[PDB]
Image: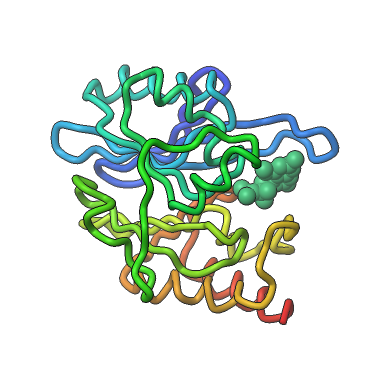
Amino acid sequence: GDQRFGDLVFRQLAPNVWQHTSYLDMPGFGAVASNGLIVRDGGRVLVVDTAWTDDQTAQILNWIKQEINLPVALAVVTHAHQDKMGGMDALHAAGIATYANALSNQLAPQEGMVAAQHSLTFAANGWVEPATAPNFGPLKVFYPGPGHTSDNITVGINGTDIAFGGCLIKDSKAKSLGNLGDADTEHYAASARAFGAAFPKASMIVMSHSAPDSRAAITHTARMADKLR
Ligand SMILES: COc1cc(C)cc2oc(=O)cc(CP(=O)(O)O)c12
Ligand SMILES: [Zn+2]
Ligand SMILES: [Zn+2]
């Protein structure tokens, strides 16, 4: 299932969909894995999230060149923290168009991130305003409300059973919601449930820090979040 490629790991989840995994030795927390996605849409490739670093993100592009060998049309990043946005410069060096929540781009400088080139905005119900996500193919971008951070966004893959929760969603056996230092404790539970309701047919839930799981990842994350209120 897992393919080791240098210091990174890649796993095919479905036809046209792979999970990328990178690791950073965070002092006091061990070597933390972070997951994103790679999607083939016809003759082009779409990326969800960078790796932790520019060098690791360049390695993602190298793997894409070896295993898919099609241009990367765009990347979308799911919030302004290092595990999701730390490799923005590598995407720009490669000529890839980059997208993030407008709020992520506003927060990026003070968070130590490089902003994406383009800003997504969202309707009151959470769905991306379509003009701000042009040519996204099967990617369906949804802002579920504040949770892990105020700017966290999520992505479904049309034509598959897959939806991606980023750092908002933890697996069905997770012991806690992890670092809540930037989190919205009042709204987390509703935001997790809003993600599940936005993608009701997704039976494979992908997330930043655990392997793909069933929808019990959503119910368990929300149930743990109920206790924050
Ligand atoms: C940004 O990421 C992290 C940073 C640091 C310094 C420690 C961490 O320790 C963990 O065990 C999990 C993460 C990922 P998270 O902040 O939950 O998105 C992590
Ligand atoms: Zn974060
Ligand atoms: Zn994370």
The location of residue 35, given as percent across then percent down, is 52, 42
Q: At x 56% / y 45%, what residue is drawn?
A: 80
Q: In x, y percent, where is residue 144?
A: 46, 68
Which residue appears at 75% of the width and 57% of the height? Answer: 181
Q: Residue at 52% of width from left, 29% of height from top?
A: 87
Residue nearest the observer in this picture, 145 or 167: 145
Q: Quadrant of residue 19?
A: top left
Say left or right for 47 vs 194: left
Q: Is residue 130 left or right of residue 113?
A: left
Location of residue 198 with respect to 63 vertically, above or below: below
Q: In the image, 29: left or right of 41? A: right
Q: Position of residue 61 (x, y in %)?
A: 38, 22
Residue at the extreme right of the image, as rendered: 28
Instruction: Tell me the colour scheme of the image.
Output: rainbow
In the rendering, at what x and y percent does residue 85 appear?
A: 53, 37
Q: Give the image quarter of residue 228.
A: bottom right
Please tell me how many numbered marks the rendered image carries: 0
Q: Quadrant of the C terminus?
A: bottom right
Residue 156 vertical position relative to residue 33 in the rendered view, above or below: below
Q: Nearer the viewer, residue 149 or 35?
A: 149
Where does the N terminus fall, quadrant-wise? top left
Q: Is residue 115 left or right of residue 62?
A: right
Compared with 67, 108 (above or below) is below
The residue located at (63%, 31%) in the rendering is 23
Q: Is residue 38 in sight in this rendering?
A: yes
Residue 1 visible, this angle:
no
